[PDB]
Image (cartoon, one colour):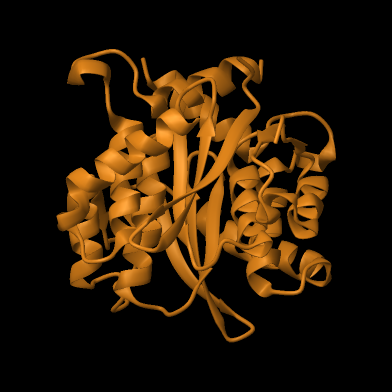
Length: 146
Length: 154
């Protein structure tokens, strides 16, 4: 597994679009409800992600928002390589599970999505000891920068 | 400085409101143009921040968006100590003001590179976090934050 590789995909709940990013080596994720499944919204999400982590390569499917000119330009500007494969998902189902679990804890889906991301990244296997995904990513990136 | 301390402020540019968080120990920042200066938008930003980093304390002023019920509940849910008082006995008040000045400087520099202010702000954040002192060697704020936090996991 490489420290700079991420997988990106869009999922759906309550007629809303959720953009999900998974740092493949750690299982860490970031997700957000976007107003429309456009290239512009996807490009905006990528720039945000690239600004906080050393993103070297992003794997995505061939959807129009992902193959868009704006996303291509954002990747060029940010120094990110895009990979598409032949024309992660084990995380979209997991995130949807946690979102179901905490859905009644907030009024809007967007808030519940963030609570679910927090829960996912802070969770320890069997809830006792070990590292969380949030701890695995800073450790992998930190040991890599030196 | 402690690995879990952040300062969060609200600034205005081109009539838009930008929320900025600075990880005091490293200089790393996260910023975003939010649609309205409300407790709801502030809380949403905080929950996002809290899910990616081990945020223990966030310093804010007493503006109505920061003292809103929704922000207090967000901090409570996330286990964040919200401090309205002047920063934790240091002199991190100078560093905390330099980033907001410095970020606005970078926003003016790249403003022509994208159509919308929101995109420019993200480009400025990227530049700020990736930037090396004098552009040669050393650590960037992005590397300092992950190193501080990783070494604190033990």
